[PDB]
Image 1 (cartoon, rainbow, N blue to C red):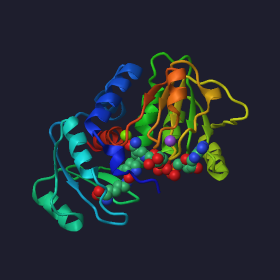
Image 2: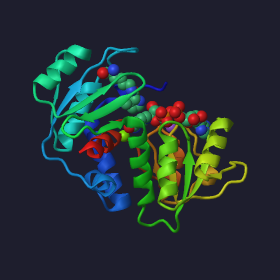
Image 3: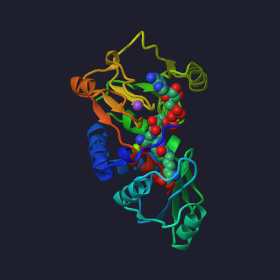
Image 4: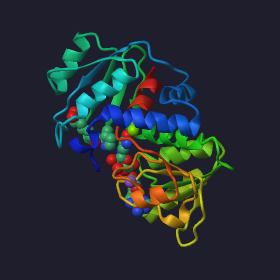
Length: 259
Ligand SMILES: NC(=O)C1=CN([C@@H]2O[C@H](COP(=O)(O)OP(=O)(O)OC[C@H]3O[C@@H](n4cnc5c(N)ncnc54)[C@H](O)[C@@H]3O)[C@@H](O)[C@H]2O)C=CC1
Ligand SMILES: C[C@@H]1CC=N[C@H]1C(=O)NCCCC[C@H](N)C(=O)O
Ligand SMILES: [Mg+2]
Ligand code: NA
């Protein structure tokens, strides 16, 4: 359970702006374009009701405001209800929400009431970050290092296998590693035997999980993980093309997936 903190979400508009430019640089597409490639969809001011939730750890400072900003950025007609929980859900439906957006400590979801489609943040995030990684314009081959094979990492790796990549997976939990190798057919990556990658997808809640031996100049590191998977020093040394943003890209993936 690695939950966002209010500090992760400070100046979310700038974080999203910067992530969008990096995505354009790496892939030639903006985030909307990535979403169009994945799902074939575009926004048309659909009304999105964002419902604060007091369950578990409770309301996270900046969370709903951040979803508010994220959804406006992508062209949705969004709003945040005054009431939380079930009273908030009611308020949202009654005020004409077409899509509901809400999270407890275990599930962040988007539910499109017009067409019944529903998205879970975890696979949506893994998929979009892996898609971004896969579209690095100047990569020499379909070879990608995946570090972290949990709720985000595994569907990301699955997506890459489906796009005919050689996927090299590592997870510190050896049982997760085994399951993923047998279910997905990924290559089990041994850090003691390192190679350089130009494409890396990382989804862990830990810092400095990408060692120097695995980097090449201008390599792409596409990572929803928090805190950052690579030190500032290694990032500067190898001119890493970092795609890393705390909420928006995954939220976009959810929303465009239910359109
Ligand atoms: N930026 C965004 O939009 C989003 C970010 N997240 C964040 O992404 C991260 C991953 O989330 P989940 O996949 O749901 O967590 P999870 O706990 O299901 O998976 C994390 C995996 O990383 C592995 N791991 C930890 N340290 C490692 C290391 N040094 N080397 C290799 N593997 C290691 C763990 O064994 C675990 O399997 C968390 O930080 C979460 O907060 C989650 C959803 C969206
Ligand atoms: C969706 C984020 C991305 C990474 N971890 C996930 C997380 O922190 N989930 C918990 C969000 C709880 C929201 C709270 N219930 C509120 O409504 O403010
Ligand atoms: Mg994101
Ligand atoms: Na990380």
